[PDB]
Length: 79
Length: 79
Image (tube, rainbow over all chains, first blue to last red; front, side):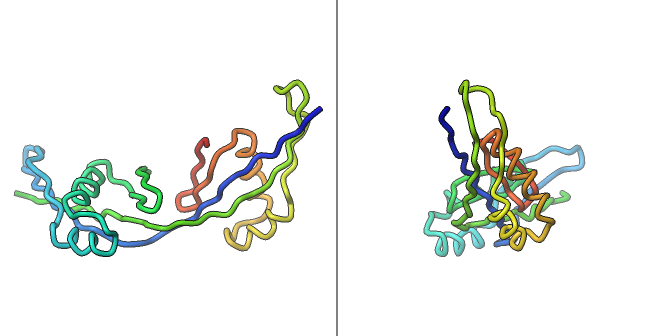
């Protein structure tokens, strides 16, 4: 009759940085091309240590699914 | 050309507390009973702010399916 213990990780992180994205939507409701501010993505690359373009494609895909991104964990999820 | 903007958020943090749980097994399939540390749970209530029991039933059910928890949005996923 052997036993075993189960471990559980409880995380809790709220609030952080912010990024403003730009999307040109027409009346018809069509989406042309999305371009995330290269400026805000530049400085963020200095505090993170990741190229800008790489960050643009990251934060970009987000605005599409509207969600949060984890760097120190490299994960992506949405509400 | 009505341009739309999205306020994305990038959270970068590393941490997380672990919880110990005792689970007795026999036929390696049936679980007689499952008890959770009422101590580590009472101390965790200070970090959550919500009643202690609420945490027990939360960290308990999770110990059954073995998974993590995020208070950032009160969610539960498998490990």
